[PDB]
Length: 50
Image (cartoon, rainbow, N blue to C red):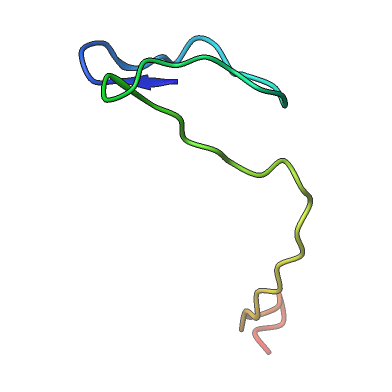
């Protein structure tokens, strides 16, 4: 819930479904709950310093 006056309503998260919002005043920001994989390569040294 992002309202131009208030800011992000850090408060309430809206679930799936059809909702009511005030045009121009409020912007919904939709984020995905889905799990996603990410691979990060990292070079690092061990205790032996290799």
